[PDB]
Image 1 (cartoon, rainbow over the protein chains, first blue to last red):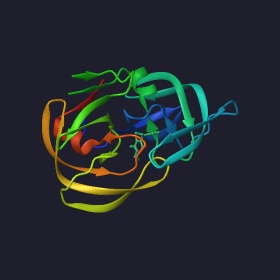
Image 2 (cartoon, rainbow over the protein chains, first blue to last red):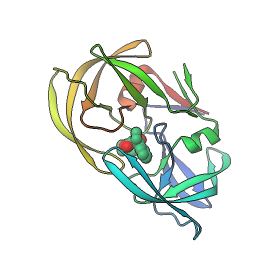
Image 3 (cartoon, rainbow over the protein chains, first blue to last red):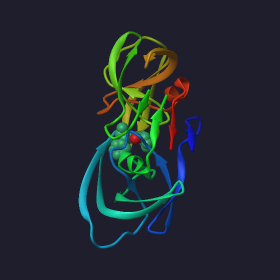
Amino acid sequence: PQFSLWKRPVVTAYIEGQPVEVLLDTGADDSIVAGIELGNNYSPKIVGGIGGFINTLEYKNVEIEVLNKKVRATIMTGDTPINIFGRNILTALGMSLNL
Amino acid sequence: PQFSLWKRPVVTAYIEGQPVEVLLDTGADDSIVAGIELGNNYSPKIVGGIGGFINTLEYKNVEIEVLNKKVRATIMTGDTPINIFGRNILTALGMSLNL
Ligand SMILES: CC[C@@H](c1ccccc1)c1c(O)c2c(oc1=O)CCCCCC2
């Protein structure tokens, strides 16, 4: 597909079966979604950005269906205002920022 | 040009002549940079990042040169840890996200 930037690149993603609304963000180094349960085998992380830091729990190798493609990648859960898919997932998806 | 996102889409843009380094952000609606001092009309404003709020000054009708294309735009200045160009400028350039 081709996403125009006139609208927020918001898609529906299926992480381990659970349906989430995610914003595709090329400035996000990682991916952080809230409100999803992914197990009792995680790693405590801390990520910073504009305005401050946020504590997160990292889960590797997680099934992800988005844009009619399934990737296995690392995601972080935590109190974030909107669910973000950073570059770690976009590269795994084969996406590009074109001019 | 084409950005692969394996290494963070960062470029040099000139804001009314001053060169800065900015990250191309597809999730941000607005744009904010640290340090530039302009004179256009401005309004005090506060924004919310993925971790907290920051106090900004907002300028309108700002001449911006990026990737060899000139534009007239709205941008914000404040003590941000990372300079980003959001969708308001991205769209004026005609950039897109493909798969
Ligand atoms: C450039 C830093 C970036 C980021 C994202 C995730 C984790 C750390 C840093 C980031 C954005 O992409 C956006 C916003 O604030 C940010 O700090 C504004 C709020 C809305 C969310 C999308 C844009």
